[PDB]
């Protein structure tokens, strides 16, 4: 199946994304820390990762920088941080796309499709 | 020879981009109509296109639908149409990214970089 990993500390976000994604026909995995995010990324072979930056054990930008040393999987940042400067940093570190919260599930899922067509 | 095509009808935006994109050492080519745009895409062989949507000779979403039949060049739309369905439409048409005006140039440049790195692969 099309595998998606969500790295987000807040269940309400993770339930909401899963539902929408499982509704669109994707298998979904989860992680609620940065550290557990990296392990799941290396074990579940996700085709796409949705990343949150405000995580309790570190900033997700360190996740993107770790990840990109060993993986080229698409990464969409979904975060409360809305500064232009936050977006620039995360894209340059290696994220592929960035949506601030609050967001529209519709826009997400479409950007999800963009990221899944180009790399695969 | 990293080549950007800007297809945008208001001049001020076009030279705002050129000032920005020429500053990182790229080559920039302008088009003010959808027709002269589609054309430049097929001809100048650019590495990316920044695509306006509100054009005099038709809708940018048709620029994409058409393009995707003969080019795979990354497309980033830059348009004032700030609507969710507008974004979904353009993306589903084969746009790679979408930034609404008004916009920060820094973020447009970082998103341009994503499209270069992902398509050189
Ligand atoms: F905590 Be995440 F960056 F919204
Ligand atoms: F005219 Be563009 F869509 F801003
Ligand atoms: Mg968080
Ligand atoms: Mg216009």
Image (tube, coloured by chain):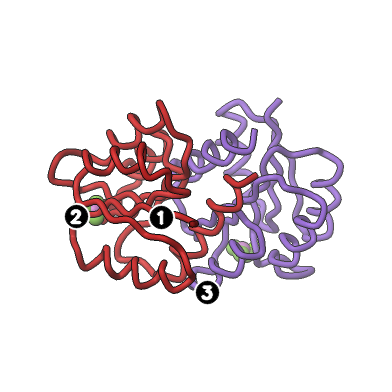
Chain colours: A purple, B red
Q: Residue furthest left?
A: B56
Crowdedness near tag 2: few (<14), some (14–19) or many (≥20) residues, C-alpha within 10 Å: some
Instruction: Answer with the quarter of the image where residue B71 lies.
Output: top left
Which is more toward the observer, B89 or A13? Answer: B89
Check disc 3 and report the residue beneath it: A85
Q: Chain of mark 2?
A: B
B70 lies above or below A75 = above
Check disc 1 and report the residue beneath it: B4
Q: Is mark 1 within 8 Å of ligand 2?
A: no
Q: Tell whether label 2 touches label 1 (CB within 8 Å).
A: no
Which is more toward the observer, B20 or B100? Answer: B20
Which residue shows up at 29% across the image and 54% down it?
A: B79
Check disc 2 and report the residue beneath it: B9
Point out the image quarter for the N terminus of chain A: top right
Crowdedness near tag 3: few (<14), some (14–19) or many (≥20) residues, C-alpha within 10 Å: few
B36 left or right, relative to A67: left
Disc 1 or disc 2, which is closer to the eye?
1
Which residue shows up at 55% across the image and 36% down it?
A: A20
Q: Is mark 2 within 8 Å of ligand 4?
A: yes
Which is more toward the observer, B71 or B81? Answer: B71
């Amino acid at each position: 199946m099309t595998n998606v990993l969500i790295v987000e500390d807040e269940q309400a976000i993770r339930r909401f994304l899963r539902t929408a994604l499982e509704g669109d026909g994707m298998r979904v995995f989860e992680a609620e820390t940065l550290q557990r995010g990296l392990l799941e990324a290396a074990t579940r072979k996700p085709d796409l990762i949705i990343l949150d930056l405000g995580l309790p054990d570190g900033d997700g930008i360190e996740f993107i920088r770790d990840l990109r040393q060993w993986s080229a999987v698409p990464v969409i940042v979904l975060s409360a941080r809305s500064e232009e400067s936050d977006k620039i940093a995360a894209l340059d570190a290696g994220a592929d796309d960035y949506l601030s919260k609050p967001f529209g599930i519709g826009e997400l899922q479409a950007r999800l499709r963009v990221a899944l067509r180009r790399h695969s």
